[PDB]
Image 1 (cartoon, rainbow over the protein chains, first blue to last red):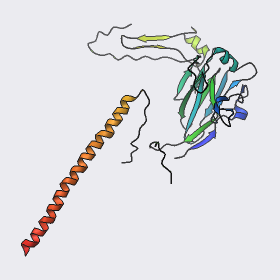
Image 2: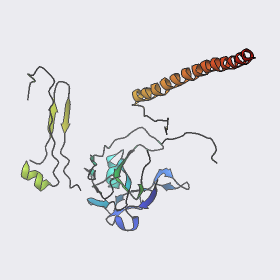
Image 3: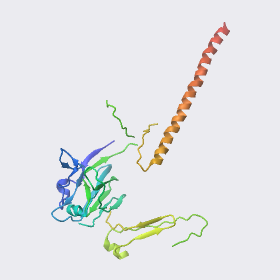
Image 4: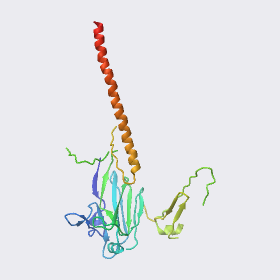
Length: 163
Length: 54
Length: 61
């Protein structure tokens, strides 16, 4: 009933110790060029260090907010070292939600020229609640979240015209 | 360990604690720890996620 | 009642999938049967009614 998309962690200001430009891949091409998702930022190390990441967001919107993030799982340790650190963790928790993630580094079957994996996660933030992201690597970070209120419906899979 | 001597099902509950800081963790308990519970049916290991939450 | 009949399950939720389908198919069967009979029975009565009225008209005369 009241859906809207807003920049939760601005690219220009939110990530001073990390690289937010180099987070593109051939797996998500835009104009035939290496790109990435608009609503998430793939953070890579700045220089030769990836310092402990710590960012939090209080929901100031008068409704539930939908947060999404991703955890990256590179195929090789040489790749892992080159993007981020060796032993890492990602930790997300609100007042309701709480999960730690641990980067499973492995060479998987090649999908879309890609031998790595990227798991996608989400949670709803209560009106007035706080959500903390913490990491030492591998965290695909949120850039855009969605503010909303639900109404108790379905999904049609059809080629039928609209009018 | 506990053997169920009651002639019926018994309901067991327990909790795993996750402190905010390593200084707190050290002061209550050791640095690297684990909790392991198993019956003949149930079996799970737990690993203390130490983090500052809301 | 306002309903969205559709539901979506993954490759590991085949059982609730089939529970959902059982709900859709059980209601289908109930409605189909009842609707058929409701028609068959009220149609008998309607036609009887019409016969009844004529009869009563001829009988009054």
